[PDB]
Amino acid sequence: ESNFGVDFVIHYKVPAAERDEAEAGFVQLIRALTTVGLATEVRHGENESLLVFVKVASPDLFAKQVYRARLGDWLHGVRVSAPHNDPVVEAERLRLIYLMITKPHNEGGAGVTPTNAKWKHVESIFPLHSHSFNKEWIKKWSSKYTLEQTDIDNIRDKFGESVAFYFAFLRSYFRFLVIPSAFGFGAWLLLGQFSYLYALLCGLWSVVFFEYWKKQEVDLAVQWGVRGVSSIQQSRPEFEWEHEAEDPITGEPVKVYPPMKRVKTQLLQIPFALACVVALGALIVTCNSLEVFINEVYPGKQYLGFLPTIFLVIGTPTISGVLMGAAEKLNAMENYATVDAHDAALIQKQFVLNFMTSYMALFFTAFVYIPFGHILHPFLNFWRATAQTFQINPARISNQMFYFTVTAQIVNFATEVVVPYEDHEEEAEFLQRVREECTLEEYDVSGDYREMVMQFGYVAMFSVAWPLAACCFLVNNWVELRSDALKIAISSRRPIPWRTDSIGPWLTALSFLSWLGSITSSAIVYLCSNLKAWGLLLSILFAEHFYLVVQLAVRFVLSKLDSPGLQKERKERFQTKKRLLQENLTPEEMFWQRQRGMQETIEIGRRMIEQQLAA
Amino acid sequence: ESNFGVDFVIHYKVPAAERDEAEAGFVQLIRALTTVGLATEVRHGENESLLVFVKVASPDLFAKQVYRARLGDWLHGVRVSAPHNDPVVEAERLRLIYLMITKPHNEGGAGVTPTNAKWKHVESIFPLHSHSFNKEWIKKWSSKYTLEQTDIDNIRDKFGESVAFYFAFLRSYFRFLVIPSAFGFGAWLLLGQFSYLYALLCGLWSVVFFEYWKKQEVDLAVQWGVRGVSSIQQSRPEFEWEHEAEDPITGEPVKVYPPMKRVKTQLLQIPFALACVVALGALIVTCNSLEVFINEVYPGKQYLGFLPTIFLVIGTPTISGVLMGAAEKLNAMENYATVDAHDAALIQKQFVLNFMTSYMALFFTAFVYIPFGHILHPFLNFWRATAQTFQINPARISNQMFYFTVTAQIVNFATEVVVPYEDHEEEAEFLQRVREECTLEEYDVSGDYREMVMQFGYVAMFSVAWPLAACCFLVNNWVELRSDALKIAISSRRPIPWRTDSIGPWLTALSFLSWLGSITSSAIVYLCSNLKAWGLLLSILFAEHFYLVVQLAVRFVLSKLDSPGLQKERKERFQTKKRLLQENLTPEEMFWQRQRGMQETIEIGRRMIEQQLAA
């Protein structure tokens, strides 16, 4: 049916082995929720838990909270002026309710942080999905392929701005990946192989897409009223501290952490990255040497020649997940005070690791085995000795790139394909619905961001080897598109509506991938079309400088596109300007007393002209 | 003595050949000045002119004007909030008075623009210098060499922010040019010639100086309350228009200009630039060929070997002034609606022309004559035929660079050195003081900006040839330092106090010069130390990538320097946050009625625990 005004739900698992302090913590949590003005209902949970609903009860405290939040946004420039001296979107009430649920006592709410606080029993605080909206969206989406602006607006109005930003980025990427597809089809059908024109077109498209997405995200931030949200610093509850100090200039009571300890912890990234590089490169070299050996020995010259590469691609997700788990553990150990800084560091680590695992094989095949033709010689001798008991065609990259995309894409498709083949006896349906709702996994969006960034990097720096690859990606994205729509619908719980300004450091990742692709496509074209080194360096010069010039030109052009957000902002500025304008409509002395008025000044001027032109 | 409250002075030259309409325009100007609330005094001018003083008389109109100005600044984010519903710096009153003097009738003031309006007799509207302040500043400065923050603050309080920004940039450049000097002295005394270490140090210093000046100008803009001033669009009075239209979204009454005509006018830059390149390159090649011929023929192998280069350097100021005059004429023809856009276009044209005239000779000597050893062959044959009636040492650049700096620097020093070797009989001293004040030239600051930018470019891309050159520049700057201090004191009239955000496009010019220097220093080092082309391209790769990496690292480091402006802004944010916080302190129904309170919720929770753990 529909919710009974329930705003947030607390799971609060209660085990029998720690009943006493669990009951004490439940009492403390109920008291802390009641002391801020939040109505509570305990109900019966499942799997030894006590789920409890909470909503806003006292309008005065809620009004104070929204006023404080809007004042904070005004301080950082999110809005124009102060709110009032004493309206709300659907996916905003949940935001302030979660704020008062988790924020400490010194800004109104009561800190019920599931980790920092003593309440170890609290582990999941979540809003509730709209059953009617979910059913309507599943019905409407069951016969739809693409996304429009209306869908993005609905996602904004329902699940905050971060999910809306992710969906807008996904739609823009899918719409811009079409030109890749047509260009690659034309190059594979007409241009031949390793075309410089295709590399130039791919670099131009990458620059255009990056700059257009920058402009589009700025436009969306201006239109959605979330411009400058990243300037707002959100305190991380899990931030451990050892010293409580004051600011020498303002007097912040700050839980300060010695920066030397954080620097020492960050220095552990270098040994970790070096060990990952060494191990993964050794595995890659072993696989490539075994592939070369079996190609030299072997009915299977073409198809049965990239089996090590296929196995490496198949095993790449497992190693990738392990490395992301290790990076997450390291980032948890690496203390951070603010949420945005911790998220940026985690994204940087994950991007570096995924870049490594997903591009080092292609880099070794393209740029390492041509100059360093003896690195795999000991491995070749070892394989020959084991079996007892060499040119390097550049085009090997192309086929390998195919075997690095289609197979993996096909495997993902196959996985999804394989699976299918008392309670008061008055509202118990709602209670059981919440019961399987709290068992859902949290909506994680960084994985899809990273996957699409890796796809963009593939298209940027390696689609020149196999132009059709982008096409495959597009098809995959289409299927993946559906896999995202239901993912937030029933496949995952409702995420907390968080205001965001952009996609984050993924923009910098995309820019770096664009530059590296502009270099790498030209390098591959020169290395495979033919060698003279000076030609390769001149090609790199031309590619990088053309990339920079095209970036500047595209920025200059897009600065004159007249986005709807900018014109809306300037119209609002006009309106407020008119509103404010209509709302508010001794000789030193006698030096200004010889003449005072109109006729006197006129006559002295006439006399001055007379005496000046009379002689 | 001191002024009698005079705020602005209008010269209003009156010739006898057009007495009638001059008198009519004088009457109209007096009426327009009186209708806004400005007290006027006509006096007796000199050289057939009618100088007139004007100051604020009615406080109500002035209050309305300052309120409107502060509202406009608030709209663009210069200040925090709206001013009031109904205080002023010394160099701010003059700004609003000039605004009401020149702005059209639809925003309070009366348009007395000396060019756009029919008043062709009005040609100079200027404020008055403070005689006491001028005398005190000359006394205090007569025994001082360098600049401090107090001098910059005084320049801000007296002559607006643009002059203050220029003086701050000059002081920062002089302070940062010291490290150039020591490094060049060490390289010339110890490192030898064309040291790669010196090139790396010069590139590092250039990056550090550029990023530090960016941070310093941001800090100054935040501290001076002029952040975001560039967002404010100032209408150019000289902007000719042919159509009056309305905005489709807001309704601006806009004097619109067809963009196709402006694009066609801008397209004239390509033929002009190409003709300048051709002519100047032909002259440079002729001079270099004649120098080579006289070096081959000739007591004067060393000293009398760069006479064509010395003559070209001596004649460079004349051609430079002619080309800047042509560029100014073209920019005047090239219509612009806003002041900032016209200024940016003029600065771009002047920078391109000065870059050409001041660097093409060195570029031809360093990078053109080595590969293109036959371009000057016909000129050499012509010189030989004229006289009748060939290796290329790279080090020729070094000496030439010396002859391209010292001589020119010496010539400038010599020029300055050469020159020395009724009126009511009550206040007539003030009147005659104004009389020679209106004859002064307007304070132009773009010339010094361009000269210092060219000096920075020299130090960036050509100081590696002669490391001592920077030292000379420093010395020159020191002398030039004095030549600037008095330049605004008595040598020029008081400029209009204009709020500015930064130095303008000179920042982009400095960044481009830094990048080009990072490339060119390495190219010169490789070409003169030795050739293999691939080595040169690898050196260019290393230099450019190291420049980019160092730029990123310096940006990252300077983002954690804690500028005083940022901490002042955050303290103000704290203060206003505290001020605002202290100033403002059917089952759907009975689902929330089974229990309501503290004891009821506690007891139902106790019973729930009992029934859950009882079975």
Image (cartoon, coloured by chain):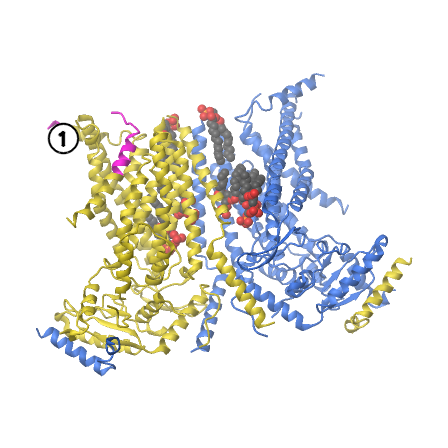
Chain colours: A yellow, B blue
| In the displayed structure image, the side of residue A81 where residue B338 appears, left or right | right
Residue found at the very far bottom of the displayed protein: B599
Residue found at the very far right of the displayed protein: A615
Q: How many marks?
A: 1
Quadrant of residue A304 within the rendered picture: top left
Quarter of the image containing the N terminus of chain B?
bottom right
Q: Callout 1: residue from which chain? A: A
| Range of magenta residues | A387-404
Q: Is residue A131 above or below residue B502?
A: below
Residue at the spot of label 1:
A386
Label the magenta part by its dominant secondary structure.
helix
Query: Which of the pair A529/A294 is nearer the observer?
Result: A529
Residue found at the very far left of the displayed protein: B615
Question: Is any part of residue A341 visible from this angle?
Answer: no
* Image coordinates for residue B269, horizontal then vertical, percent: 61, 39
* Image coordinates for residue B353, horizontal then vertical, percent: 62, 40
Question: Is any part of residue B226 visible from this angle?
Answer: yes
